Image (cartoon, grey):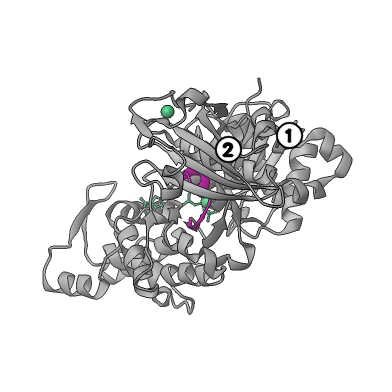
Amino acid sequence: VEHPEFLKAGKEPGLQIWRVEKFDLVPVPTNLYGDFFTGDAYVILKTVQLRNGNLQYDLHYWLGNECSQDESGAAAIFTVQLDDYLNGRAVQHREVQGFESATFLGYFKSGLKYKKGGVASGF
Amino acid sequence: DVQALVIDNGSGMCKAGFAGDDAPRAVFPSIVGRPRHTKDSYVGDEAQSKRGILTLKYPIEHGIVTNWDDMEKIWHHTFYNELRVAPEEHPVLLTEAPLNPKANREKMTQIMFETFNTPAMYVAIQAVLSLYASGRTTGIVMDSGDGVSHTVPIYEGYALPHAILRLDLAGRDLTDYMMKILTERGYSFTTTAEREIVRDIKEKLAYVALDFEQEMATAASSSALEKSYELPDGQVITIGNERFRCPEALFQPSFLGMESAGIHETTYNSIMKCDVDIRKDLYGNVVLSGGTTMFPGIADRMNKELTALAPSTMKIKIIAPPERKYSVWIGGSILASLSTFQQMWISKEEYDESGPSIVHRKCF
Ligand SMILES: Nc1ncnc2c1ncn2[C@@H]1O[C@H](COP(=O)(O)OP(=O)(O)OP(=O)(O)O)[C@@H](O)[C@H]1O
Ligand SMILES: [Ca+2]
Ligand SMILES: [Mg+2]
């Protein structure tokens, strides 16, 4: 698959975050990176530049404690799809609220924040 | 805007519905009935209820279709009677058992396009859909339904075929076993309506003991473990250690005179067939799915048994969602609803161009 946001994914070093919104992958405004709705699921792509010029990828799907099944399932599938699109070069990481990996946490300079709420389930 | 359909073809029960719904709209027996000695045929609940004048057939065995004529009837009925749709108007996602023969995948594809004129279709592995429904891309799924129990290791979205294993024992076997052991108590359940009573007893009173021997000692010592069951008339029966001896067969197949390993060992064995580098992720993500995994106490027991087989430093985690009976179907509903699904399905054009073999290049 080649979704519009997939075309934007992993083009240069940096962080990209999308939120699952009713079965679609929606970009999160850069000014809000780090602010996660506990009732939502997100997909985070960390692109790191390698010495030979190619890019290293780590895909993290973050699951809020109250996100609905369609959101967590969609986040997982979009992650497999994004990896496939990126020629299988991404290491996938499941990140559950309150149990995130040091690596994921380390992507947020000031530390990530949790906020109650989110977009309604797509079911 | 188009509406996709999701059909999970179980050996025992078919689950059908619309992508986007959180549950299948129709769940019915995967049975085709025909006039016994001489409507030409019936499907599902109606076939089952008219068994007195019909000869019944189950076209799916161990998740694999064994009769395509009967399968077409189930699908025809599913579309027109259960879902009330015109199939030529909807993309259709179908599920398949792990290791489904290549010939069978092509057949299913040909039937959809040629017989039903579906505008598009896709085939997904049941176990994988269940893993997705649990919000994971890596884990090992223990899928136990009607006739077979599968252990399917999946890494970053894809099953590892070489490590898929199976126990030829599942729900119908447990129902038949409960039938047998209840006779030792002095109860005769032999007819179809009687077998249905036994299934209900299995589904309502059975449970998996954390420690079987100790559970047996408890039952023998007192009546603490006894439960009462009221038959359709009013007769009340008493069931004891049969409550846990029945599902114990999943862990001790010798109970059914089978030589194969129980489900905990099959799971451990599948894990050991995978690269050491990913085994940690499998042990930490054991997902249970299917009707036969619905017994109370099964997750606690799987945790205990797997913990005994794995190094003490291995973190064991059993995931048993309450909705695991429809996990496969739910996973399909989500997949079929994604904005990116429209590109993964096989379209009519593609079928016309490449034929049934296109399924191996679009669905893997
Ligand atoms: N609460 C329950 N406790 C124990 N068994 C249950 C329960 N609910 C359903 N079952 C059993 O699960 C089985 C049906 O499961 P399921 O619907 O997952 O199988 P299927 O889709 O038809 O099979 P398969 O995947 O083998 O093709 C039957 O044997 C049924 O009695
Ligand atoms: Ca939400
Ligand atoms: Mg099934």
Judged by depth in the image, the label closer to the viewer, 1 or 2, is: 2
Q: Identify the residue position indicated by label 1 in the image.
A: B120
Q: Which mark is residue B239?
A: none
Horizontal arrangement in the rendering, residue A49 relative to residue B131 (left or right):
right
- Which secondary structure, mark 1? strand
The reply to whether callout 1 and callout 2 are in contact (CB within 8 Å) is no
Ligand 2 is in which quadrant of the figure?
Answer: top left
Question: Three-letter amino acid code at disc 1?
Answer: Ala
Part of the protein shown in magenta: B130-144
Q: Nearer the viewer, residue B133 or B145?
A: B133
- Let me know if residue B136 is in the magenta part: yes
Q: Nearer the viewer, residue A115 or B298?
A: A115
Q: Secondary structure at mark 2?
A: strand
When the figure is inspected, residue B255 is found, relative to residue B4, above or below; the finding is below
Image point (26%, 46%), residue name:
B233
Q: With respect to residue B157, does B187 lie above or below?
A: below
Q: Which mark is residue A14?
A: 2
